Image (cartoon, rainbow, N blue to C red; front, side, top):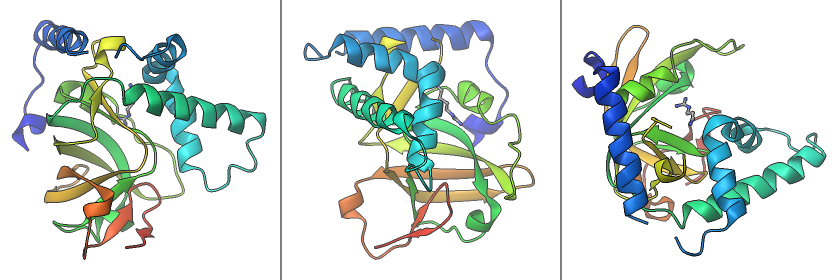
Amino acid sequence: FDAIKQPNRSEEEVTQLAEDFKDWSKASNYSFITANEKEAVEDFSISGYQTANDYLRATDTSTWGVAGADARQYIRTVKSALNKLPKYKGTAYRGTWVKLSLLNKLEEGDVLVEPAFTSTSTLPEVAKRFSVVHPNSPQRLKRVLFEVKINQGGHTIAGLSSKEAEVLFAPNAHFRITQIERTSNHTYIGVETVKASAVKNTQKYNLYSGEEVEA
Ligand SMILES: N=C(N)NCCCCN
């Protein structure tokens, strides 16, 4: 996991790489994409992901109201747009917070299911930015830095945004664990994208709630 652990590259080099990825993204386009779809994706990266991901993670969305209908529409529009954007395959990174109770159970070959959209960056510097602050919660959480091998599901949204080199998955993405390294304050987890329907005879867990997902 030294790609993650090592010191960040300079602003200049990271900004350059992000710009090159944005360029590659645009160059790799799509003609079917709507104005509402481009606009939803631009908004997504800045603020929209906050509402969409809360909706996707919510135990009870009967309480949301008119805002639920808007959230469903937004999610549908973002998923539709994603399918029209260029695929990315290669390595990407994501920093997040996970229940220690789940982390304690995890082994290589277990599958993690993200109920929200999954946003990753090709730049570990950018990934590390989004997990700096410890959230407040009833739950004991620990910082997790994922190294993600992407061979399906990931689409670049960097063409439509930003120096984030962002690659996005639709909700319910499944990730098979290939390696775990546990330390104090940081757990590193290597994962590979897998198709849900190809997951057999292993244990799946919901990455947010920590609950087992039915085989
Ligand atoms: N990596 C996270 N924890 N969050 C991703 C935020 C997505 C912003 N474009």
